[PDB]
Image: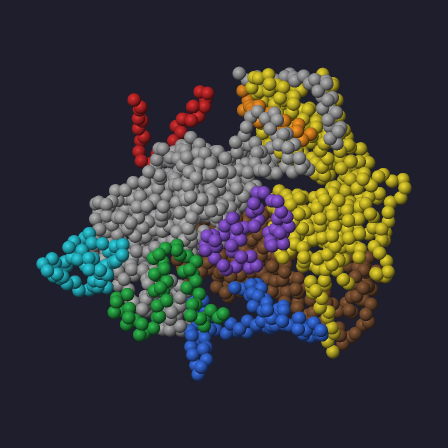
Chain colours: B red, D green, E yellow, F brown, G purple, I cyan, J orange, L blue
Amino acid sequence: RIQYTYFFPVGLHLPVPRYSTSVSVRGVESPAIQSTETWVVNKNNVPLCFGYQNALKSICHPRMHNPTQSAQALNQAFPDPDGGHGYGLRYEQTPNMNLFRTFHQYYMGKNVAFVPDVAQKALVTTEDLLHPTSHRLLRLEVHPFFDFFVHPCPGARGSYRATHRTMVGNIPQPLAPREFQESRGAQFDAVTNMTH
Amino acid sequence: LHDYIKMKAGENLPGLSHGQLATCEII
Amino acid sequence: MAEYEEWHKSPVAAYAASCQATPGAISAMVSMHQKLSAPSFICQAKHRMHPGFAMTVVRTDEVLAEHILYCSRASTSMFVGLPSVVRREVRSDAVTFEI
Amino acid sequence: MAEYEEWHKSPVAAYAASCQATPGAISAMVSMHQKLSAPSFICQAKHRM
Amino acid sequence: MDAHAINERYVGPRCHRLAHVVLPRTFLLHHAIPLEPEIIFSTYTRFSRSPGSSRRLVVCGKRVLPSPSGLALSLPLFSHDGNFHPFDISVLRISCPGSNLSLTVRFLYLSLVVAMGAPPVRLSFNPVNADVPATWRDATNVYSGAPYYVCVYEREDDWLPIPLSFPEEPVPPPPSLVFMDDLFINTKQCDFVDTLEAACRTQGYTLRQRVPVAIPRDAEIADAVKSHFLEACLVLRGLASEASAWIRAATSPACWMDVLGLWESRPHTLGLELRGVNCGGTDGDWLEILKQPDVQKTVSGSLVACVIVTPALEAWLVLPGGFAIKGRYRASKEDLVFIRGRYG
Amino acid sequence: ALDKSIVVNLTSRLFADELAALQSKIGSVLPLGDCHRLQNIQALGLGCVCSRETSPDYIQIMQYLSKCTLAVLEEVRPDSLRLTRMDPSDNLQIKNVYAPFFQWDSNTQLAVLPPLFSRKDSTIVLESNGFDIVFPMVVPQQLGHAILQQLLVYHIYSKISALDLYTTNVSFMGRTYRLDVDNTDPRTALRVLDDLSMYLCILSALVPRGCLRLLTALVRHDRHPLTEVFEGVVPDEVTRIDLDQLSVPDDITRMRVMFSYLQSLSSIFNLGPRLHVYAYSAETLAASCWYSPR
Amino acid sequence: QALLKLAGHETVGRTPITHLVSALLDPHLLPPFAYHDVFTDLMQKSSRQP
Amino acid sequence: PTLAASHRVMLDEYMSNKQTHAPVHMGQYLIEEVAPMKRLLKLGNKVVY
Amino acid sequence: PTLAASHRVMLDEYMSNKQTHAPVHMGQYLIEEVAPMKRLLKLGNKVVY
Amino acid sequence: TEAGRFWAPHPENVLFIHKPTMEETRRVALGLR
Amino acid sequence: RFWAPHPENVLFIHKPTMEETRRVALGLR
Amino acid sequence: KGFAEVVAMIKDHFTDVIRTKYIQLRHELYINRLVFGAVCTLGTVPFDSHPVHQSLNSLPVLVFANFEAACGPWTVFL
Amino acid sequence: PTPVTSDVAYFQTPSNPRGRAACVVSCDAYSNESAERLLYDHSIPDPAYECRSTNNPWASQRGSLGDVLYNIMYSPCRQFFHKEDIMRY
Amino acid sequence: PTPVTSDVAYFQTPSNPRGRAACVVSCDAYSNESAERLLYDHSIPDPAY
């Protein structure tokens, strides 16, 4: 009994200069619509659908939603990371209400400007994050729902901690581009059937 | 600066799938 | 303000600094504030929306293949012993021999 | 008001909050109050509705 | 709310009175207590104007899911010779069994004692019940400034208030007797730095290498290593902590190490144990120090100094660059009875 | 009569290094999965539950062992293990090989226990097949219980601690032996301690008052040999129960009920199947026991 | 009036699901300027403690 | 890979003409299957082996 | 299922070309038959098996 | 990693102080103090 | 070029800047 | 499963019964009530022999084959 | 789950869904220090392509969602993501 | 009668007009309490789709 394995994707987004080859189709040419399904021919030649409602029994599950299972394997993957500049870690609260005092202490003698991990991903195109000249822009995209960074604890060496993205726009441009968000918003239009 | 452009380009391969790799040029 | 303990987590502002300022672009941002969690995906299956990620399906399948076995001459040299019969079980219904 | 013992029976109102207010959408609402009976089906099968 | 009535039958008789305490999340966010069901609580109290130690007790705690909401506990109160002392700290120690987590939560009795103020034969059957009603009374912690709730359950009782025995003259000021621990450790730290500054004077205000680490050739780097020694003197004096490294070396029955966060770029991790390294001071023993993952980044990197304490209370200040200065914690025999009693 | 044996197919082969252990431990006892004739290696290993990649469960191994059949090795071939099985009432001949050496005699009472003195000693590995054959050990019942006595004391005083010479070591008469307890899974041993707690507090509510009064008249007047568990100091709690008057017809309705629960502690202090020995030799190390389960 | 057709009407427990589908409707997200006492209306309609 | 066609069009065009079908259209796409077994596909009576 | 073209054009396209007939057009549709017997279909002089 | 090879001329550890990151952490620490 | 490790490598600490650091640590305590 | 498991399994077969006696008998409780059950050992079934479903006048009755019988003492459990 | 800008031209040809091919037949014998650099290193491109490093970086890397779920019923993704069961080859 | 949003691709392949497949050869022998779950228990999807 020979046993093969098969794979097929669903729900992608082609790049911007869209093209065609066929001449028989007239009704799906508009780039405002995006498919959310694929069709797979069954054994008895019955074309079955595949939607997210048929894919909901393994997305909505807490194995898909906690980094404690993930940040213990990443910690054994690279055990001594460079403890980076502690830029966007936390809120150092001080008893001030003069915000012009807090405005002036921080920008007075600053001479070298830092760039965080996530802010240097939102300017990269969709291909340079996948190009092999970049490790650190690619190593810290471990999980879809979450967002990892380097924390100075414990000791003098670093460790990896986690925040949740909570939105769609907190996924960066190289993994969900600009024109995808526009075509997703046009799908928001025709479902609820609003008028601008 | 020469150590920067060298960072943006790049025994390093332990395996290769499709075959013995071949070099190209640029004219 | 720190950018990691925040709702708006800087790649939001990268989109808004590169729009066209078109009345279709407002419909993106309203649909961009979407709680990318588990029990909102239920509400993106009742209306056939697209959540923020594609996926790859993986299956298996089986085939009753009738095979062809070839084997050349004298690849094996056999050794056949002599058979015997051993008794194990005595019950009220049966006596079990086995060769 | 009782929603089950009524002429208008709430799935009418779902169409009202989802129109586009088009002059073709008026003629939908004229034909939407079509009596769903047996001796009305004669009058739509004559004109082939 | 079950953990109050469980503790009255198992921790209850082993004490004199219990302090039923419910901690809100505003207290939990300040002390950073990650609520898992694996947590083992341990309680002991630190007496004053007496030999200070009470025995350690394990108290059960459960999360209360919703009128307050948070972690529920029960603190022991000890009455030696028939009365309470007002300035008498009850210490809650929180730890996980497997991972690396140790938290000290400290309470004072005047925030608790005041808060309590307004034929076959039969076998009895007395199960644990939450039938007794609660009376929620407010409080504030003196040490952190985060509010916590205190239950008062209904049962020579109504006639008398709760006995207190206020201290007698001559007495140190109660801003100095409340923080007995933070004024004892701070003077030991301030006397530790004075040994390091005296060790520069005998050498001629110099810093000698001890660890063989090559230094890149720049004059600004040689000025930068000097700035790590002066910044470490602002930190070791300002540090007054319950769980420092030399305290674990005094109550040890092995080198005890704690790295520092210079210029407030890191939080301090204190009490890291060097297992299997004997700090003898010979050149063979510094290589076993260099196999540690911490010491490689305190020397090759920057912004982190490191303090390594022997069990003979002799300590080195390791700077980035391999530079080190031998210093000594001075603890008298009267001081070790004070430390091994309250802490160890 | 009844003609029995078990031959076991090793699926590929086995080496000459790992054969030196399987040849050295001939005549030993190991369990196996089902009472077949022909057999793979993946039933003979007791360590299908005593794994290396996970922490073992010392009660669950012993709890596994009253289920399965037990078998004796007699021959070893480098592609096939030839054994013999144990019928539930069958006079066989066992040989004393087991490395922590405890002397037997005629009319002793054996017991089959999980390996607790050394894990690495009783687990030999067979990496020609990717499996480890794990041996149990036979122990006379003076230590058949006295290890399970010490093991239940250890899991009590681990939670209180989280000293190290009283909670671990097992004292046979004459010597001590260190247990091999470093990384265990006690989540099925604390159920056993949750099955002592029901029977023990019931035995603290119907304590007969006459036997309480005999302690008041023995720990301070005379000097019994085994009253020296106590000192001369009687517990204060005994006098706080003693104060009620005696009742002879209610020291029968308390003695009979207390007597019935001490039939119930043969349900939590169970061993595996037992081996009634009736003939033993001293210079051949060969016994001849009588197998009878439960 | 365009968001409410996706969010539905059913409830998990006390909380309606409209507080959970979109971050534009979750009151724990505040508008980034407050001239009114918004800080006290948030606490009495929240199982999420601020 | 198997037959995936993100709209109903592309699967009902690959059945029509095997050669002149598009693998990539503007909105949708088709993964033409490269499989170690081939089958008879009968969607109606048009057969693409 | 049998032949059922929801407008007169679709049945006159399945006759004219068996391969490139539309199974589903914009408004109407067609059901190409999958039947245990299969007949000849003479509409004029064009024949589709 | 040997006692006789202690004072190697090129030992394996090299100091590397990134002077831009050191000035920004001084200056904030001089702002709070 | 890197410097070579040697136990006679010294860093001379200024007398005033060590005592001016002592003035700050008094006040912050 | 052996005698060391079933006594730990019968207690989980009577979880909702022990709670519905001692709460019902807490106003008055007698020492002669504290015995709660007794387990005997009736005999052995040969393994791989299956019970057979059977309905009799109705009444569904399982029937075993090759059951050899024994006896045993009554043992208290609680 | 996969980034939305994965490539259709990847899904046409028979490779694994990791993005990096797990053909560990090609590397040297018993070099387990060197046979990890095909599965999880990203300094080099994948053995399939020479312009991109990884199609979906949500499932290729150490700690990513392929290593979380399926790397330790039946799962056909146990075939491709398990580290120890590929090192047998 | 059948809803207006009944999918046309159901009518292409030889099913039955119930909507659910009624193949009772597939289920177990002599189980009337279990064969009914094919026909009318609408928790499971129908055995076709």
Q: Position of residue I27 (x, y in %)?
A: 27, 56
Farthest bottom residue in view: L57
Q: Position of residue E202 (x, y in %)?
A: 74, 18
* M8 over A109 or under it: above or below: below
Which of the two residues, F182 or D4, is positioned nearer the viewer here? D4
What residue lies at 71% left-to-right and 48% top-to-bottom? E147
What residue lies at 74% left-to-right and 55% top-to-bottom? E137
Q: Position of residue C11 (x, y in %)?
A: 48, 38
In this picture, residue E106 sits left or right of residue A104? right
What residue lies at 63% left-to-right and 29% top-to-bottom? A104
From the image, which quarter does the N terminus of chain A lie in?
bottom left
Which of the two residues, C57 or L6, is positioned nearer the viewer here? C57
What residue lies at 62% left-to-right and 21% top-to-bottom? E224
Q: Position of residue E111 (x, y in %)?
A: 77, 49
Residue C60 visible in rendering? yes
* D45 over N7 or under it: above or below: below
The quarter holding residue F206 reads: bottom right
Residue F99 visible in rendering? no
The quarter holding residue E134 reads: bottom right
Which of the two residues, L8 or J31, is positioned nearer the viewer here? J31
The quarter holding residue E294 reads: top right
Farthest left residue in view: I45
Disc count in the image? 0
